[PDB]
Image (cartoon, grey):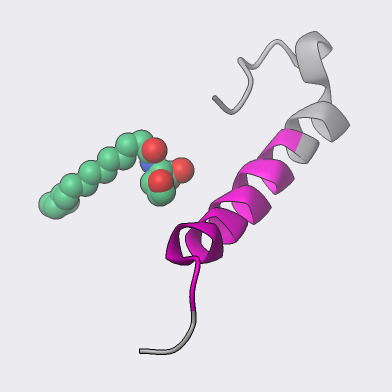
Amino acid sequence: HXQGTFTSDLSKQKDSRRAQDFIEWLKNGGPSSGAPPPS
Ligand SMILES: *C(=O)CC[C@H](NC(=O)CCCCCCCCCCCCCCC)C(=O)O
């Protein structure tokens, strides 16, 4: 009861992770990394 937008309150956590993972991949190298992207 209370709270709302449950899928968003999970999405922010998956986005912090996926975004930090994607920023890691770009920071680390991006297409130049060679590692496929976190996807
Ligand atoms: C949010 O989406 C977190 C998970 C996400 N992974 C993926 O998107 C890939 C698919 C993961 C499927 C996991 C299914 C687990 C089923 C239950 C297993 C119970 C037994 C386990 C025994 C060891 C991510 O980004 O990490």
The residue at the far bottom in this view is 1
Task: Look at the image and say whether residue 19 sits in the magenta stretch.
Answer: yes
Q: Nearer the viewer, residue 9 or 21?
A: 9
Task: Look at the image and say whether residue 5 sits in the magenta stretch.
Answer: yes
Tag count: 0
Seen at 35% across and 89% down, the residue is 1
Left or right of 34 on screen, residue 38: left
Q: Position of residue 33 (x, y in %)?
A: 77, 16
Which of the 4 image quadrants contains residue 19? top right
Q: Position of residue 26 (x, y in %)?
A: 82, 28
Seen at 63% across and 49% down, the residue is 15
Which of the 4 image quadrants contains residue 37? top right
Is residue 2 shown above or below 19?
below
Is residue 19 shown above or below 33?
below
User: Which residues, given as a range, are shown in magenta?
Assistant: 4-22
Q: Nearer the viewer, residue 32 or 5?
A: 5
Which of the 4 image quadrants contains residue 13? bottom right
Is residue 29 shown above or below 19?
above
Seen at 54% across and 54% down, the residue is 11
Secondary structure predominantly adopted by residues drawn in magenta: helix
Q: Position of residue 23 (x, y in %)?
A: 79, 38
